[PDB]
Amino acid sequence: MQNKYMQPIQLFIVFEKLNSKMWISKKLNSNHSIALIPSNWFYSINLFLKRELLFSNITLIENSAIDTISYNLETNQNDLDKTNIENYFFKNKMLVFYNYYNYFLKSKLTLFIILNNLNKNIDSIDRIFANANWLERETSEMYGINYKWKIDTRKLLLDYSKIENPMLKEFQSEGTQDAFYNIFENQVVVLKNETVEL
Amino acid sequence: YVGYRGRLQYIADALKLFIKGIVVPEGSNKFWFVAIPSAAGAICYTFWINSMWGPSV
Amino acid sequence: LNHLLAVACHALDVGSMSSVFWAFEEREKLMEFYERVCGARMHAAFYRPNEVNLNAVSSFLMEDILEFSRNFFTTLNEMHNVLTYNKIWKQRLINIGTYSFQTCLDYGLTGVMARSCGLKRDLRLSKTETYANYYYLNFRSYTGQHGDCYDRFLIRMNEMCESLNIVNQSINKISKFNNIVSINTKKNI
Amino acid sequence: ALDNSFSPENIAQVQSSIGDKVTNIDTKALALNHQTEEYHKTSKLVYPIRTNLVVE
Amino acid sequence: QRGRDYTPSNKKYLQPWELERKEYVELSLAIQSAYSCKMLSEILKDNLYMLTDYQLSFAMFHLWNHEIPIDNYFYNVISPILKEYITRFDRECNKSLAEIATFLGRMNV
Amino acid sequence: LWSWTINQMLTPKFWVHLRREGFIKTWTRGHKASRHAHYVGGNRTDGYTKQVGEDEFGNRYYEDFDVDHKNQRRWVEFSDYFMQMWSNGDKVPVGWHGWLSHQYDDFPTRTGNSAFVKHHYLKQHTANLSNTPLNHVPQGAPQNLNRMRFITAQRDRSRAPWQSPKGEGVFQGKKLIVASNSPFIDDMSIR
Amino acid sequence: GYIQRSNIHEEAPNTSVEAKHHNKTFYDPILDIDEDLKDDIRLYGRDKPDELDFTDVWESSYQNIICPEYFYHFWFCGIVYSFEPEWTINYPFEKGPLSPLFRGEHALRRYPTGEERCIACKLCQSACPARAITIETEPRPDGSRRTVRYDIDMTKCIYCGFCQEACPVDAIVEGPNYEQTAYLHEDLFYDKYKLLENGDKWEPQIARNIEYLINQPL
Amino acid sequence: RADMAHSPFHKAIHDLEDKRSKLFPDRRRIPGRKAKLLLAASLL
Amino acid sequence: RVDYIVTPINAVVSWARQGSFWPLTFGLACCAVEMMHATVSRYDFDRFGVIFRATPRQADLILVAGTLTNKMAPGLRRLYEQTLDPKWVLSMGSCANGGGYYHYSYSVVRGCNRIIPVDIYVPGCPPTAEALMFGVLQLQKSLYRQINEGEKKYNKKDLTY
Amino acid sequence: MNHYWGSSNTIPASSTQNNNYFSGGGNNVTIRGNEIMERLPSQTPSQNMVQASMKTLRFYRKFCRLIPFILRIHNIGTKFTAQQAMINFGNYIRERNHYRDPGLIDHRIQLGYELLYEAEMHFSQHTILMQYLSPYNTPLSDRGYSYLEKVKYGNKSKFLQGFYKGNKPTEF
Ligand SMILES: CCCCCCCCCCCCCCCCCC(=O)OC[C@H](COP(=O)([O-])OCC(O)COP(=O)([O-])OC[C@@H](COC(=O)CCCCCCCCCCCCCCCCC)OC(=O)CCCCCCCCCCCCCCCCC)OC(=O)CCCCCCCCCCCCCCCCC
Ligand SMILES: CCCCCCCCCCCCCCCCCC(=O)OC[C@H](COP(=O)([O-])OCC(O)COP(=O)([O-])OC[C@@H](COC(=O)CCCCCCCCCCCCCCCCC)OC(=O)CCCCCCCCCCCCCCCCC)OC(=O)CCCCCCCCCCCCCCCCC
Ligand SMILES: CCCCCCCCCCCCCCCCCC(=O)OC[C@H](COP(=O)([O-])OCC[N+](C)(C)C)OC(=O)CCCCCCCCCCCCCCCCC
Ligand code: SF4
Ligand code: SF4
Ligand code: SF4
């Protein structure tokens, strides 16, 4: 950590009604900072990021989600401290995280948003960051997040005429149906799934 | 290797092209689908008449 | 390897044919190096966390890599002669796909696509984001003032050429150039 | 089958039992190698490298 | 580092396992990259608190291997560090002592 | 035909090979190893490459250091050369496979100090036997005529059906009397 | 972890002639003519020079009136590159370079006495990333810990090598054989019979490679 | 530093005049020489 | 009898179709690169007279080289059906053979043989370039022999009936 | 309107006209439009089950208006009549009619529109997409059905029918 680093406190100085929860770790890069952002302010915060002076040169590197409902500390349970970020995973249905890179500040900024509503509603930002379109499409299809005000909600990387969210911990890697060829129908069909257990 | 040191490769490919089966798409026009290549072959094999191999050969 | 395949496929799509064979010969040599170090010419599965197969690493492998590096200039020049200055190639690529930094920024463009805009963004030469011996090697990264396919092709060629310099520096970092010199004769022992 | 730390007689007996005839089973050689640590067999490639030819 | 004390546990000389692996590796890479006595002395003085006898001997080996000329910067900055470390050496520093002495002799300082 | 071209037969190598090996062998070398016309018998013209060795299937292996490319030093000459596209790479025995692949510079030597172990349980090399009756048949597969034994054994590993009495049997009231099938001996009852 | 630096700039190497490591031929006047072309706005952007010269006219005339592509490139490639020896390897009669680390076809080895080296520890089964190995073991009548069923699904297995790496007794080895083409999908369901047969056939070369691999650490 | 001249890392520095002359061009391209030659020759 | 003429003509037809064996330009995954490596100079495919054609109508071999996904299986079936007869199918790679590394996946078909009849299988992940060359040459030999595998019986005059 | 469903996305009736010399019109409701769908914006949020129900009814109306074209292009008219397909999809919706979450309903409607567009554009296969249109308990109209089970188990409880049928292979 022998570098010059400054917290991205501009967001919370401007959005004066929000509380700040920020982290930095040596597990990340020296210039990488994590923060907690509420969903109802996520869209406005991205609006501010996309056009603030020092945050103008910001690109949305990555976006995804975590099914925190089934998250459990498998080892060193007692070592957990109240300041750790893992404390926000427990009992929360979903956690959608975005990661941006800023060139002026040579920094990486990750924002975590907790989704507790059962339908997983959150405002999309693909209208602010263009590359977020396919990222949010993938996230919605794989985890079932209901993005709102999204440019294109059509599936991306999922099969035709199928509805599912495979990346949820409830889903099984083997799937629920297999595609074979039917001679009677003289074409590919899909039927129930029987697999091999090692 | 098609013929010792590849001496009959063109013969092999011509015979294979003869052997390969053909099917006309149902939506396509059966008459024209075959008529056009026939006319093209006739024209191509008429090409050689317009060739000279000497002062008046 | 990646730049050779990308440039070869790009040339094949545009129409040039023999570039694929010329690039894939060098790809075969590099795959031979892969197989020699890990036994798989593709999908090496070599790097693993906090462990290294030191036995596989051999000096003769380094010497063969040096020979490949010396001969790679010939393949680069062969491709460069038929692609770089060709009028058809210039008319096919120049001013096609042109984009600004803002597009580079808006769509999260990175690597060659980003550097073709002049963003000057390389993660290997970053103070807080370097991950290997790169930060302590004196090599050069290239960017273009035109964000078009021609600039991207030139950047890929230059990066292929500069990988040779980086490999040479890396191999020199593990080389014993000097030797004991006799006091009486002032010659190597 | 057996390590040199074993008796030469035991080594020879095991080799004979497994029907090995392409290995040095000499009792004296085994005794000399008994409890001895040494590097693997090496050969020499002699320069210049040239192709073997049948000129006559 | 934060809340870090670099005083050797032996109370004689620092050891590689006391430092974090990242610091040791990065300082070694910097020493290897140094191509002049001036820059090598700058690096060594800047990171003296993390410097180890192994890395000092390796720096001497690098200078000898690349035939980096010995000059005023060496004799004025590097030499005191070598004197201090060699004085603090002991039986277990035989490798570092032999390496440093041999490479200094070969460089013919 | 023309296993040996005119320009190759006009060289000393062809005449020496004809004198020693014979016309049939010298002419069929090209058929056995159809490679570049100038490589028939080796790249050099003053003589033909000496035979490195021969394997159990009659194949002859050669090594020439004057080939124009590095990856052509070592080559094979197959015993079976009935037609082109006939002999395949699977015909190389285990010992010579590595030598051809350049894994090591040692080659099998018959009747001499060898670099390869010769255990008593070793089996002779076999080419690819797929598309042949002597192909790998999984136990219990439909092709395997003894699939019933394997299937019954697999079923019994988890659940062995009870062998019910068949045919006429002794009856004691409403009970069928059958001797116990347990291999174990009832020592307490016996003594 | 990180280090502290005082002089960010890496100064250029000494240019004095007397100093060692001086290269008198590093710069070539004929070649290093960059300065002439360096000041050209066309290189830096879409703009054009204030004053165009007849040199551009001559260059454009040469490029357009006399199209040099069909001659320059035709010669340089067709006529010259055709003079190089072919790079082809005659596969049926020659094989490409391999290494003792090559992972080809799986096989099961034996001790020189003929006993199986495989003890049913299932380390290979657990390490197999693709779940391609199935092992069932029962005590042998003599009492040995030996497997009763050892199957490798060659169609489901990625030839990574994890099986031989995790094997503690070098029982399962991915020998060099790669010409294992099969016409029936069932022929790729390798069983213990198939693996033991492969080991018996390929033991010489496998043992030869293992010798070098074991000796390398020494 | 290898990217700059006279670096200690460079090794091929002594008596490279002949080798460099053989390996690299000894000529410079005049901008319009080929154009003028070809056009005048074509006209005549 | 027709056999007098059929048998030599059968041999000629088999030789011609073996010499000219054009696969389809179709690659799905990393196995594609291996196919390209076989096509390129180090292991020239052209030596054995195999040249790739883009359209299925002009293809004799279907190289299933790469993983097959449920989203693609109908496409593979359509391509196979649209390829002009006679034709053969060669599966390449573990993924094409039996699902490979993704046999326990929810998207990948457990084998291209479920959608298509696979004439030959080439194990590997990826199969070596020489491995693919061996598979293709074995397929060519089998193809040449398929015309007359001794089905018809010989009568007292040695003529098949 | 710059949308796939816009009134200007119709296929022209002629090379030089739209269906007339005095008027401009085209069909885009019962067939696919002229330009492909580049973007499908998310359904505007519904704050009420009333709005959610209206969205469901409108989506079902669009599906019913499009089903004959889907059947004709996919050559599945023989398997079921247009009305039969409509009723089968109605049963599909009825099974889901218990929903009471507007956000979930909006997500479901988005998915339904996407799958409908795929069916229009032939992205899906007929055998793969007919699973939604297939009857729940009636035989397919293009096949001969077997009533052996009904004859054997006439006037018997579903439990007994399942007991006789079995639910596990008997070989192992
Ligand atoms: C007395 C006069 C007698 C005249 C007889 C004329 C008729 C027979 C001539 C045959 C010559 C070629 C050998 C054919 C038999 C091969 C057998 C074989 O390999 O079996 C395996 C063979 C398959 O294995 P393969 O390795 O793939 O076959 C190799 C190929 O044949 C490819 O390899 P290849 O070797 O077969 O092809 C060679 C050919 C390559 O040709 C080509 O590529 C052109 C092909 C053009 C298309 C032709 C289509 C023909 C279709 C025929 C269909 C069957 C007809 C059957 C009719 C039966 C009638 C009873 O060119 C040559 O090399 C010509 C050889 C003759 C040159 C003259 C020799 C002397 C020169 C020096 C003189 C001075 C010496 C001074 C010495 C002084 C010493 C002191 O299976 C068969 O049995 C099929 C055989 C098919 C043969 C095709 C022949 C094509 C060329 C025919 C014309 C050649 C010119 C004749 C001129 C005659 C002028 C009078
Ligand atoms: C019957 C059997 C036939 C067998 C045929 C077998 C096959 C033969 C293939 C032949 C192919 C052609 C040769 C290619 C050589 C390539 C060399 C190369 O890589 O450099 C390229 C070179 C330019 O590249 P570079 O020099 O590397 O550029 C870098 C420079 O630093 C850049 O410096 P820069 O840009 O400032 O100027 C450089 C310039 C040099 O510029 C100057 O120095 C010009 C200075 C003057 C400027 C204008 C001012 C006016 C000057 C005249 C003033 C006169 C009046 C003075 C009045 C004074 C009053 C006081 O360089 C040039 O010369 C470029 C001009 C390109 C000419 C194109 C030649 C086409 C040849 C086509 C041959 C077709 C053969 C067909 C088959 C046979 C017939 C059926 O271009 C050439 O020189 C092309 C070759 C020119 C001819 C030399 C050879 C002549 C003899 C050919 C014999 C062929 C064999 C058969 C003969 C018949 C036997 C019976
Ligand atoms: C004898 C010492 C001097 C030798 C000098 C070299 C001369 C070589 C001449 C060409 C080869 C001639 C036939 C070789 C023997 C073949 C025996 C046989 O069974 O044939 C089956 C072979 C079978 O074919 P094949 O064996 O060539 O190939 C089939 C096998 N595959 C598919 C693998 C390639 O028949 C033939 O040889 C092919 C037909 C040849 C027809 C032309 C014959 C020309 C004869 C010229 C003789 C010249 C002699 C020199 C002196 C002349 C003086 C005037
Ligand atoms: S090679 Fe890898 S995937 Fe295949 S059986 Fe061995 S360990 Fe399993
Ligand atoms: S092959 Fe090796 S790792 Fe696998 S069960 Fe046998 S002894 Fe254990
Ligand atoms: S078998 Fe292996 S190499 Fe081939 S496509 Fe599948 S993962 Fe890639």
Image (cartoon, helix red, strand yellow):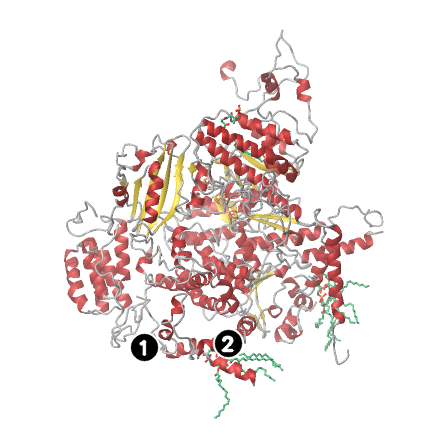
Q: Is residue B44 above or below residue C132?
A: below
Chain under disc 1: G
Chain under disc 2: G
User: In the figure, is residue G87 to the left or right of C178?
Assistant: right
| Residue ranking furthest to the top | F173
Q: Position of residue G2 (x, y in %)?
A: 25, 52
Residue G24 badge: 1
Q: Alpha-carbon distance for marks 1 and 2?
A: 40 Å
Same chain letter for marks 1 and 2: yes
Q: Position of residue E13 (x, y in %)?
A: 17, 52
Look at label 2 and name its amino acid: Ser
| Residue ranking furthest to the front | J22
Q: Is mark 1 within 8 Å of ligand 2?
A: no
Q: Earlier in the sequence, mark 1 or mark 2?
A: 1
At label 1, counting other C-alpha atoms closer than 10 Å, the crowd grade (few under 14, some 14-19, many 20 or more) is some
Quadrant of residue H7 in the image? bottom left
Q: Which residue is mark 2?
A: G61
Q: Position of residue I63 (x, y in %)?
A: 60, 50
Q: Nearer the viewer, residue J123 or J73?
A: J73
Q: Nearer the viewer's eye, disc 1 or disc 2?
A: 2
Residue at the spot 59% in from the left edge and 73% down from the top edge: F47
